[PDB]
Amino acid sequence: VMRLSEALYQTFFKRSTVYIPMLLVGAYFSNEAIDYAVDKMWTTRNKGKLFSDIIAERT
Amino acid sequence: FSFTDATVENMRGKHDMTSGMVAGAVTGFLFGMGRPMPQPVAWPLAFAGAAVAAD
Amino acid sequence: TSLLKQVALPVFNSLATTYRSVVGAKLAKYGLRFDDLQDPLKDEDVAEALRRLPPDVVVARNCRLRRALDLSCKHEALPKDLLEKQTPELSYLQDVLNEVRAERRERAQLGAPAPYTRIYYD
Amino acid sequence: LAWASYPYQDEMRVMGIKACLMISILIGFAAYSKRLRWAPIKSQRIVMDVVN
Amino acid sequence: SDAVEVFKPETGLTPTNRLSMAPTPYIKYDEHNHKRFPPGTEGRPFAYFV
Amino acid sequence: PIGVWSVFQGYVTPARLPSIQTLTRVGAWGGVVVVGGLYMVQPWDWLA
Amino acid sequence: PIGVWSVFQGYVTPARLPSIQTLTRVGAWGGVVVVGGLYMVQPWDWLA
Amino acid sequence: RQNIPLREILYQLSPYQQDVIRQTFTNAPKTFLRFFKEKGVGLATFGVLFFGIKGYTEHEMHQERLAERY
Amino acid sequence: RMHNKIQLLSVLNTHLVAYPTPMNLNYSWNGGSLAGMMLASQMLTGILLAMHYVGHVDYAFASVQHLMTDVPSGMILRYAHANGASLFFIVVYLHVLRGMYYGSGAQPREIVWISGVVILLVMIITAFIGYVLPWGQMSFWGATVITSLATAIPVVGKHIMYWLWGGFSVDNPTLNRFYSFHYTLPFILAGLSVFHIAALHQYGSTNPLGVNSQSSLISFGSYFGAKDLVGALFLALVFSILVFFYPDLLGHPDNLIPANPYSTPQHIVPEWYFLWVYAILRSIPNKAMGVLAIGLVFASLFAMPFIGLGGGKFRIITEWLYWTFLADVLLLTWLGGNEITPITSFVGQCCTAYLFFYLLVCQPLVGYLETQFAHG
Amino acid sequence: RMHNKIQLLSVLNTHLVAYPTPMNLNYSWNGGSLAGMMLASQMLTGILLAMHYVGHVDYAFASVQHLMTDVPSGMILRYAHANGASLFFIVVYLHVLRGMYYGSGAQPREIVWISGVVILLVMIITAFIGYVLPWGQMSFWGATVITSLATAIPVVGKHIMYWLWGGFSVDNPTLNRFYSFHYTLPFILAGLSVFHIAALHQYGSTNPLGVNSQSSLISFGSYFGAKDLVGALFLALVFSILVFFYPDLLGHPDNLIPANPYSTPQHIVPEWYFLWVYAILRSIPNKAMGVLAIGLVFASLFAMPFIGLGGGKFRIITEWLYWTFLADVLLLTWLGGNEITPITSFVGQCCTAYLFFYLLVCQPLVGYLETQFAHG
Ligand SMILES: CCCCCCCCCCCCCCCCCC(=O)OC[C@H](COP(=O)(O)O)OC(=O)CCCCCCCCCCCCCCCCC
Ligand SMILES: CCCCCCCCCCCCCCCCCC(=O)OC[C@H](COP(=O)(O)O)OC(=O)CCCCCCCCCCCCCCCCC
Ligand code: HEM
Ligand code: HEM
Ligand code: HEM
Ligand code: HEM
Ligand SMILES: COC1=C(OC)C(=O)C(C/C=C(\C)CC/C=C(/C)CC/C=C(\C)CC/C=C(\C)CCC=C(C)C)=C(C)C1=O
Ligand SMILES: COC1=C(OC)C(=O)C(C/C=C(\C)CC/C=C(/C)CC/C=C(\C)CC/C=C(\C)CCC=C(C)C)=C(C)C1=O
Ligand SMILES: COC1=C(OC)C(=O)C(C/C=C(\C)CC/C=C(/C)CC/C=C(\C)CC/C=C(\C)CCC=C(C)C)=C(C)C1=O
Ligand SMILES: COC1=C(OC)C(=O)C(C/C=C(\C)CC/C=C(\C)CC/C=C(\C)CC/C=C(/C)CCC=C(C)C)=C(C)C1=O
């Protein structure tokens, strides 16, 4: 039913030497997004208890 | 039903109607599993409705 | 022992029939028989009894084992029309295997070995 | 004193949250790639002359 | 070469012999685990993207 | 199976068991192990 | 007799040598190891 | 490599001509019930023996502690 | 064709890529790959920890602490090693229980079962001498209690005890020789695992049906690589949870006290994976009889392929008795962690007697009756 | 047959008892079994040594002294482990020179030669980092001079150097990680030795005549067991002489001084088996060019099965040139123990140039001329 596009296949999928650098940039951005989400959730939950909150409070 | 009710009770820290609805949904889904399909939705609704009427 | 061992045999027969009923109910869903549960690798007498058989019997046994293994991979059972036709207790091997084991017991009383060994690979 | 026994508990928990999320996504992706490879076998048709 | 001298089949209208002499184009696969796509579905598969 | 299945199938007979002379000559290796241990440890007052 | 013996005997002709397309497809692996090393180390904006 | 005499017709479909995980949601409650139907007796006898012997032992240990009191 | 030109490509292709395997193997056949992966993990993290550990009684605990706090990624490595030992024992115990359930040690796979029992004994010794290396209170006192079982042997007991200690008590030479033996024994485990796997490839694996499977075989590399990856990821999830969220859950708090030979703890207990052997030892009020009972347990494990009849699903009486055996070994695990008490002594004695009854009476005799029921 | 029923006995029989070997092999084919015996001896002595050695600064020297004077048979174990490295290198060097003389790496035994060169590199690294362990002046200063040679690679220099050291100078982290790496590397040596022997068994050994020997093959296990035992007894005589009569003859007296990072010795030279590489490095007045030449020697060693034409006798020009090569290598070994002098610099440069000339010009071109003379 759902099917990968031919023009998108001929560019990023037909050769491994083009597929691998695309894989590495996607891996970089996926790690950045996961880091951002985990850090935002942790800092939102534990607000007011961290050391940086005390330091920014003393300014 | 009783274990799911008291578990949601102790997890939420308060007594209200949500624990009964969740326990009813779990018990009715246990009853309704493996049956054709009005039933895996209809039986959680019936057991949750029994919990709501009880409250 | 002989006074109580006269009637200890019907109790054995009743337990054996109950056991075969339960296991044959388990076996029939896979299309298997009781004689298909014997492995030529596990027993050298069964390996000897299997080469004494006509080729169509061996072809049927291999077909049944292949069907059962395919059913086991698919996490399925036989359909109802096939399941009602299954005969789990129709023997094809017990006479030949009984003859093989009797021959081996006969050779052992005269100090002779069996004229075959285990299946050795590589 | 509880900090003194486990000085890196916060960093360990942040790393554990990231690891659990990543492994939970990878479990689904690996289950997908397992079922894709095993699909021609799980749906094969065998017809034989044996009825029993 | 002839199939009677090379494959050496049994004689009869068995289920395997019927498909050997005339195979059917209406092949039925098992669909308990996977439902097939409509036959002749073209295009590069979506599983590469996944 | 080969251990207890062979006893239960009646394949272990007196004519198939090893002889008493074979059991005597095989069991003579027990003195070799004793004298080997005495040679290794030398825990004796036997030399006098 | 694999190596210099192959070229002394005349077995390495203009034919049986890799084509330009084959060398380019093999030569395209040079960018992959560079990108992989830059991905592993990440020296961002380190180019002078 | 171990010639096996067999007569069959085998059919196989491409893995890009069928779905991958969509039937997994339909069969999941049935497989759960089938698993517990097949392994119900063994898990129950394990649970009965383990928890009964553990409970009897813990009860008699508590009685032993109470018997040492003054 | 390319693997036909080099030997190392051919051996790898035959035994990893194109090796035939039964198509109906379920997820109970993943314990071996997981055990191999856990051995590789233990070897890697141990090699990395050995660059910061010092095997001296004045610096062992302090170097452990310094590795925990000051070495970058040292806490991850130390917790990964200490909890990977427990996950290694979990995976191996489940592998052995799979073999006990299906009767996989039977002919023609007696060598596989025997090399497995050898592997398990080496694993037990490796973990026991590795636990002494932190030189905590449990590390000292468990080595004292267990190596004092050699005095149960008459005449030459104390001499063997003093030879193993290097002195009159557990002290620095014991720790140094334990460190050398502990570094060494995992490589013997790797060799034994290679031999154990190459023994199985002679005939192949058994299947969950318990029948001959030579008619339905598929390539190992294309199909069971992904199926092993799935189980490896489920194991990595549990490993991550244990390392990062509950790192001292499977440990003991007394091993964080430095060792004191003049004040014993109130409850000397081992790690959880030695608790059933410890319960067998504590249940019998005689040291020689307890050591003999442990040796007879392992002798019964060696003699399984020759006295055991009875296998998987279709052999239903032994299949039902398997769950009683499993409940018995978990009751032995629980009883080891509890103190000595008349009811725990009685229950441990009964549980040990039932383990011997199942191993030596149920497996031959009930197996023979069900073979006569099914094929007589 | 009894060996036909257990797969372990079949492999052992096939590869150690009934293996067909040429009957005209002389005593220069005993290098490999002697090298394996020396590897096993080093592993045994070291595993025994590690039960009394402490891998920490301010304990290492004292632990070696306590091993020497207080451990029963400890002096024998230490001197055996120290001189066994020298005898191991003597045997492996004579093995390599045999292979150079006879052209043993040619088709179809290129994998055997390549795995040998890999084994030699791992042996060199193992011996160097094991020489660091006693923590004397020679240990510290040799480890300083060699590891601070990564500042020849541009840009990525001192980063790699400081990551190797675990700090800013050779100190306790360097010694502590060198202990773990040195314990671990000989098991890789044993595995590579097993692979190396298994690669030879695919095609069997060459003979002193240099002709096909398939017509005249005899069993290994009867005829070449006693022949190996004779050479092993000669090696045991030399080993016993070195251990008991001249235990410090091959060493350096400066390694009996505790290491001082602020005072350097007058002459810093390695052990004798590293001296030819040291002379090649020290002769070239550039660090990066010296490391490039050292790498080029081993690259030319790897390329030898694909460029080297010419074997033993009946190829007489390359046979004569082998003795010039042997003299060149022994001269480089002598030059490494001297001081830096303009005449020694000139002679070392000429020796390095001739070594490259023989390895890269004489072996292909003179060998091709010999083939054109003999069969042209
Ligand atoms: C005094 C000290 C007080 C301590 C209080 C805490 C003790 C422990 C907590 C309470 C435990 C009791 C309920 C445990 C339920 C666990 C789940 C379970 O059993 O399901 C498994 C299992 C589930 O099967 P599956 O779902 O098929 O796996 O359930 C069963 O099969 C039922 C098990 C019933 C057998 C155990 C009954 C309790 C034993 C008590 C024996 C007392 C003897 C008294 C003799 C002296 C009298 C004077
Ligand atoms: C063939 C021989 C087989 C032998 C079988 C041996 C047992 C194998 C299974 C054992 C199951 C694990 C139990 C470990 C803890 C026992 C503690 C104990 O008895 O002493 C209580 C012990 C002391 O109690 P006290 O001395 O009585 O106060 O308490 C503790 O130390 C805390 C117990 C924590 C329990 C954690 C449970 C969950 C951990 C993770 C579970 C993972 C399951 C598998 C998942 C991975 C799959 C690959
Ligand atoms: C080449 C392989 C291995 C090496 C070099 C090694 C090394 C070490 C070292 C240096 C320690 C002390 C550091 C510490 O206590 O955290 C240790 C601890 C330990 N090792 Fe390993 N090990 C290896 C493999 C294994 C294996 C296969 C096991 C199997 C069970 C194991 C079990 C343990 C245990 C239980 C501890 C005690 C952990 C604790 O409670 O702190 N090790 N190992
Ligand atoms: C480090 C420990 C071990 C490793 C790496 C290992 C590895 C393996 C592997 C890869 C398999 C093939 C597939 C499988 O069944 O998972 C296997 C099978 C087997 N293992 Fe283990 N094993 C280990 C320990 C043991 C132990 C401790 C035992 C028994 C006491 C054992 C007994 C068996 C048996 C009987 C089989 C054949 C089962 C069958 O194919 O049905 N193994 N092993
Ligand atoms: C610990 C190190 C080594 C061990 C245990 C070892 C072992 C052996 C053995 C047992 C043999 C067969 C008997 C013999 O010809 O001596 C052999 C042959 C051979 N080895 Fe070694 N070897 C080692 C190192 C090396 C090295 C360093 C090289 C080369 C750089 C090498 C190259 C060869 C070659 C080419 C042969 C075949 C000789 C022929 O058949 O003409 N080996 N090796
Ligand atoms: C498992 C194998 C081995 C172990 C455990 C081991 C262990 C040790 C230990 C603990 C030391 C320091 C104590 C001392 O120097 O007296 C040492 C030193 C040394 N090791 Fe070994 N070793 C092994 C194998 C080898 C091998 C294969 C070689 C050579 C190729 C080697 C070469 C050396 C050398 C040259 C020294 C310096 C000895 C000295 O000058 O005192 N070792 N080794
Ligand atoms: C059908 O059945 C089968 C399986 O089941 C489904 C399998 O899974 C496998 C594959 C086996 C695996 C993954 C187990 C791993 C194997 C072993 C022998 C474990 C021991 C090996 C170790 C620890 C290697 C680590 C040591 C090294 C690298 C040496 C040191 C050197 C360096 C660090 C450089 C096979 C062949 C199989 O047929
Ligand atoms: C906290 O502590 C403790 C442990 O620890 C974690 C324990 O396990 C145990 C109990 C464990 C038992 C009964 C099972 C393991 C039993 C033994 C005997 C382990 C084997 C080890 C021995 C005999 C030590 C000797 C070492 C040798 C011989 C080195 C090996 C080298 C060669 C064979 C060459 C207890 C009580 C304990 O309180
Ligand atoms: C007096 O001075 C000198 C020494 O001193 C006593 C020497 O010895 C040497 C001899 C050393 C040479 C020729 C180089 C040795 C080779 C290498 C590659 C250097 C060693 C590399 C190290 C220690 C990097 C860290 C790696 C380790 C520990 C192991 C890596 C692990 C694996 C490969 C699995 C010379 C020349 C010297 O003049
Ligand atoms: C050209 O013809 C040939 C030769 O030339 C005549 C040879 O020489 C050899 C090879 C010689 C061999 C294999 C014997 C030499 C010994 C070696 C390599 C190892 C030395 C080991 C010893 C002395 C004992 C080791 C003891 C133990 C217990 C370690 C094992 C560990 C465990 C079991 C855990 C071969 C194959 C050959 O074709």
Image (cartoon, coloured by chain):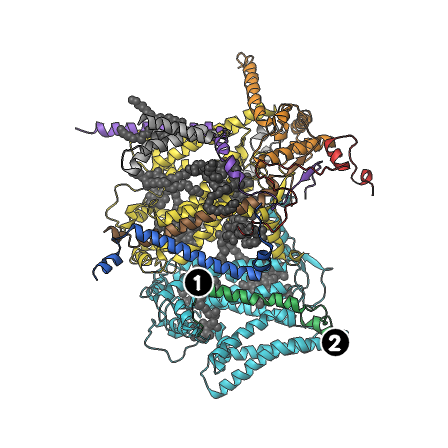
Chain colours: A blue, C orange, D brown, E red, G green, H purple, I yellow, J cyan
As rendered, which of I238 and H62 lies closer to the eye? I238
- Whole-angstrom CA distance, mark 2 to mark 1, is 49 Å
Q: Position of residue I87 (x, y in %)?
A: 42, 45
As rendered, which of I351 and J214 lies closer to the eye? I351
Ligand 6 shows up in the quarter that is: bottom left
The mark that comes first in sequence, 2 or 1, is 1
Mark 1 lies on a secondary structure that is: helix
Q: Position of J71 compared to J199: left or right? A: left
Q: Which residue is mark 1?
A: J182
Residue J329 vs D45, above or below: the answer is below
Which residue of the protein is positioned furthest toward the left in this rendering? H70
As rendered, which of A53 and J74 lies closer to the eye? A53
Mark 2 lies on a secondary structure that is: helix
Q: Position of residue C83 (x, y in %)?
A: 62, 25
Mark 2 packing: few (<14 Cα in 10 Å), some, or many (20+)?
A: few
Q: Position of B14 compared to C23: left or right? A: left
Q: Does the closest atom of ligand 6 sit within 8 Å of the Cβ of label 1?
A: yes
Quarter of the rendering containing residue I205: top right
Q: Position of residue I129 (x, y in %)?
A: 38, 49
Q: Which residue is mark 2?
A: J372
Type of the residue with mark 1 = His
